[PDB]
Image (cartoon, grey):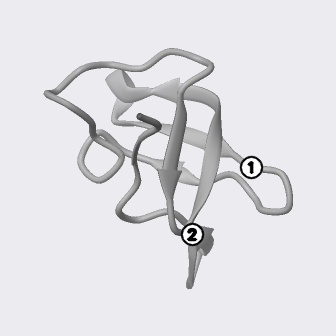
């Protein structure tokens, strides 16, 4: 398990991208990266997830809000 740190969020445009040291940008979406209730997230959004490796590169899948 590891943590990711937004590079910028586009929840409104359909998604937000995460960026983590030692890894690449973790794709983020209010469906898996969601959190307590359907809320929006701004820069600084720290989340917890497990990046895996799929055709378009590594990516988080069942991410969540850091605490």
Q: Earlier in the sequence, mark 2 or mark 1?
A: 1
Q: How many marks?
A: 2
* Residue carrying label 2: 51
Q: Is residue 67 left or right of residue 52?
A: left
Which residue is depicted at the point 20% across and 31% down? Answer: 36
Q: Residue at x 57, y 41 (%)?
A: 17
Q: Is residue 24 left or right of residue 32?
A: right
Instruction: Please tell me in which quadrant of the rendered image residue 41 appears.
Output: top left
Residue 11: image quadrant is top left
Using the numbered discs, state the Cα–Cα distance from disc 2 to disc 1 in whole angstroms.
Answer: 10 Å
Against 40, is 20 above or below? below
Residue 58, by quadrant, is bottom right
Q: Please, what secondary structure does the residue beneath circle 1 have?
A: loop
Q: Which residue is mark 1?
A: 20
Percent across and percent down for residue 12 are 33, 22
> The N terminus lies in which quarter of the figure?
bottom right
């Amino acid at each position: 398990m590891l943590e990711g740190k937004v590079k910028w969020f586009n929840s409104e445009k359909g998604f937000g991208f995460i960026e983590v040291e030692g890894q690449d940008d973790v794709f983020v979406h209010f469906s898996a990266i969601q959190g307590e209730g359907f809320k929006t997230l701004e820069e600084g959004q720290a989340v917890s997830f497990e990046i895996v490796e799929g055709n378009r590169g590594p990516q988080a899948a069942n991410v969540t809000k850091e605490a």
